[PDB]
Amino acid sequence: APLFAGTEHRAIMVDSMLHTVYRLSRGRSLTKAQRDVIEDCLMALCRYIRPSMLQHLLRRLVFDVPILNEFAKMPLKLLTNHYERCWKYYCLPTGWANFGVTSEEELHLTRKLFWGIFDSLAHKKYDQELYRIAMPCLCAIAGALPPDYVDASYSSKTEKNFDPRPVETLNVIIPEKLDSFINKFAEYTHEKWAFDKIQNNWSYGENIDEELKTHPMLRPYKTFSEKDKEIYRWPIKESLKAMIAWEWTVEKAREGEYNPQPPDLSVVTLSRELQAMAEQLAENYHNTWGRKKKQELEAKGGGSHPLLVPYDTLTAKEKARDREKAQELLKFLQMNGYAVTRGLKDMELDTSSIEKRFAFGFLQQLLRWMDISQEFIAHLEAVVSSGRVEKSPHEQEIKFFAKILLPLINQYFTNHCLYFLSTPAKVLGSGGHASNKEKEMITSLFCKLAALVRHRVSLFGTDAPAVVNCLHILARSLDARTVMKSGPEIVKAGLRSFFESASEDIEKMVENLRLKGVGQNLTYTTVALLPVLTTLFQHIAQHQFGDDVILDDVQVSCYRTLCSIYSLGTTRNPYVEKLRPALGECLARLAAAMPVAFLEPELNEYNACSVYTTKSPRERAILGLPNSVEEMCPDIPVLERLMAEIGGLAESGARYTEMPHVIEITLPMLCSYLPRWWERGPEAPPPALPAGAPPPCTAVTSDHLNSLLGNILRIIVNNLGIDEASWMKRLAVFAQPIVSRARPELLRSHFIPTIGRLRKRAGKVVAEEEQLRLEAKAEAEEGELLVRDEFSVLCRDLYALYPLLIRYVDNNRAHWLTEPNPNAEELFRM
Amino acid sequence: LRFFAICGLQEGFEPFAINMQRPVTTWFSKSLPQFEPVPLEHPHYEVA
C-alpha cells in the first residue's frame, strides 16, 4: 500500500481498483476472515492514496453508507480515518501541503454524507455498536467541513438499489402549443447538429460515416423526411411530456424563431429558477437513460453503470454533459415564448448565504433537538415524580441526544471555537468569522442546555459529566459582546435569565450551607453551576467582554452572586470547609470580569458601566436597587479595609486555621481585582487620556499590588513547614498575575529571607539524610521515612514559592544584568 | 547591540560580525526581470 502515494498518473486504474475492492468487500458468501482481509486491504489503500483520488469512492459511499445497515460498519470506519487524516485538505482555505485543496463537488459530497448519516441515525433505533461507530465518523466529517461552507447546489427538496424511475412523461398529455414547440426545437436542434457537422467539416453525403465525414440526412427540414422529423421530435416530445407530468405550467407568449441555420440559443442566459429547472430536467433525462440502463442490467443479469447516480452526486463535467441538452431545450422554450414556471420550494432561503452556511444548519438542528430534549426531559421528570414509567417512549431520543449530540457538540465547538469568536474588525482564526445569526444561535444553545440541566443532574446520571463538559465548551465559545450589543431580545433574555437563575441558585445554596430540595441544589451547584459559571466569567474576563455583557440586570445578578459568596465567610461548617476552593475560584473570576469597582464605591460616579450611571434615578426604583451604591450589599469591606486586614493578619503571623476564609476567598478575589483596575485607574498607560478622559473610577496603583504580594509572601512564610497545607499551590497560582508590577525593593525585603529559610531547611534535611547513611539498616528505614516526609514538605514549600520567584526574575533579570546587583548575586547563591 | 548583554552574551553567542575589520557585504533580491538559460531541471519547461 505505501507505494500508491503519488500514483496520479494511473488515476483511472487506481480508482477502478478501489471500486473493485469495495465491491468485493460488499460481497455475499464471504467468510468473516475473508471479509476482514478485504476490509484491511481497503483501509490500507485509503491510508496512502492521495485525498483527491478518493473522490469517486466517496461518491459511492455517499449512497451506500446512509442506509446504516450491517454493511455500513466498515465504510463508517473508513470515512472516519479518511477525514481524520485529511481534515486540512477540506477545512483550510489553502488546503493540505503538496496535496492541494478540496473542490466544490468534494465539499458537497461531504455535506451530503454528514447530513445523510445524521438523519438516518436520528430515526435509527438505538444500537450500541452502531452508535459507537457512527459518532466518531460524524465528528470527523463535521470537523473536516469548513464552518461557513455554502453549498452551491443547495436545495430544500431533499428528495430521496439506485432508483432510475423517471416521471410519467408519456403518460401525461401535451398541449398543441407545446407540440408546435416540439417541431420548432426539432428545427433548431437538427440545424445545430448540422452546424456541428460543418465545424467538423461534414458534407451532405450518402451516409453518416464519420471516416467519410459525411451526413446522409443533411437537408432542410421540409425535405428532411416526415418520419425522421418525428424521430427527431420524439426526444422533445418526451422532454415536454415529463415537463407537463411535473405540473410545470408552460405558458406561450411569443413565437418561435444543407446549410445549417440554427437559431442561436446563447443570446439569453437562464435565470436561477430556469437554471435549476434545466438541471432537474437533465436529471430526469439521465433518469430515463437510467431506466434504459436498468433494462440493460436486467438483460445482463447484473452490472452497475459508472454514472448510475443522482445529479447532485454527479460531478460538474458529467452533469454538464446532459446540462447542455436540457438547458438548450429550456432556452429555446424561452425564446419561442413558452415561459414555463415551476414554483420551487427553495426560494424561502433567497440570498441568505448565512442561512446556507453549514454551521447555520447544524446549529438549527441542534436547537430543534434541544426542544425535543425539553419535551422528553419534562416527561421523564413527571414519570419519576409520579406514576413510574419504564417503557420510555422517548428512549431512542434520550439515547441519541446523550450518545451522539453531546460528544458531537463537544468536539465541534472545541475545534471551531476561533471561528465563532472572530469579528469583522478582528479575525483571530485561520479564516472566516461567524455571522451574527450564528453567534446568537450558539448563545441560545448554551442557555437552553443550561436550563435543561438545571436541577436535573441526577436525571442524566452518567451523562451529567458530558452535559457539563458541553456547557464548558459552549461557554468558552460564546460571543457575549456581539450577542448583547446587537441581538434579538429573545436571546438577550435567555442570557439574562441564565445569569439570574444562577444567582438565585447560589443564594439558596449559600443560605442552606449556613443553615430533596437541599440535596438537589447542593449536588447541582457543586457539579454543574459553579464550574460552568467560573468558566463563563473567566472567558468574559479574558476576552474583555465585561464592560459590554455585565450591565443592568446582569450586573445586579453578578452583585448578588459575588456578595453572597463573600457573605459565606463567617460560617465554619465542614461543608463550607470543603466547598471554599471552588467558591473562591468563582469569586476570583467574577472579580476579574465585573466592570464595576465594588471595593471602591466612593468613586462609582466616575464609572460609565455602573447601573447607577446607566439607569436613571427614576429607573432603579422599578427594580429593588437601593438608593446608593454602597448599599448594593455592605458585607464586603472597602479596598482600604481589606488591605489593612490582610496586612495586619500577615504581620501577626496567623495560620490557615485562623484565616481560612481570607486565604481561600478574599486573597484570590483581590489578586484578580487589583490587576484589572490597575490598568483602568491612575498610574496606567494613558493612550486614550487626551480625549478629556474623566477621572478614573478606581484608586489602585502599583503600591497596592506590591503590598498584596508582600503580604502573600509573608503568609506563605508564616505557614512554611506545616504538615498539611494544600492551599499553598492555589494561592501561588492566584497570586502569579500580580507579580508583574512588583517593585525592586521586594527582592531584598521579602524574597531574600524567604529563600534563605528554604535553603537552611534544605541543608538541615540533607544533613539528616547524610547521617542516615551512617546509621545501620534497621533504624535507617524509620529515619528514611522521616527524611522523606521532611523533603516532601520542603518540596511543597518550594513548589509554592518558586513559581512566584520565577516571574519576579523574568521581570527584573534585564535590570539586574544591566546594573550589577549584590542582592541578585545573593539570590543566585541561594 | 541593544539586547545582546541581556540575552545571549552569557549564553555564549558571539555577534555575527564580531571581529570583521569591514562591514559585512549584503545582497538583495532585485526585481528587474533578466534573461537566463532555461534550467536543465525546470519542473514545467523543457528545451530539446
Image: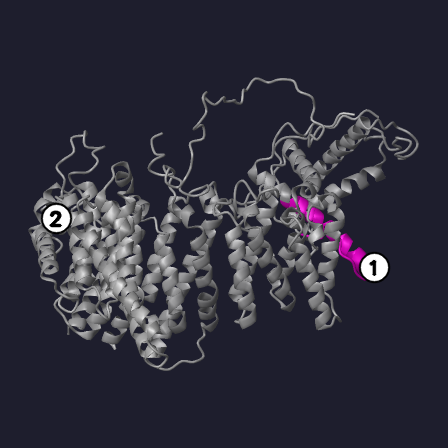
- Front-lying residue, A765 or A9: A765
Instruction: Name the residue type under label 1.
Output: Lys
- Front-lying residue, A204 or A77: A77
Residue A817, image x, y percentages: 29, 39
Instruction: Name the residue type under label 2.
Output: Glu
Task: Work out whether A535 lies above or below A129.
Answer: above
Q: Is residue A112 visible?
A: yes
Residues at marks 1 and 2, common chain? yes
Horizontal side of residue A594 vs A411, given as left or right: left
Check the picture and name the quadrant holding the N terminus of chain A.
bottom right
- Say which residue label 2 marks: A619
Nearest to N terminus: mark 1 or mark 2: 1
Separation of residues labelled 1 and 2 (CA atoms): 84 Å
Q: Chain of mark 2?
A: A
Residue A287, image x, y percentages: 70, 51
Mark number, residue A300: 1
Horizontal side of residue B37 vs A693, given as left or right: right
Circle 2 SS class:
loop
- Write down the region rendered in magenta: A280-309
**Could you tell me which residue is drawn at 73 percent across and 41 percent down?**
A236
Q: Is residue A295 magenta-colored?
A: yes
Residue A562, image x, y percentages: 18, 58
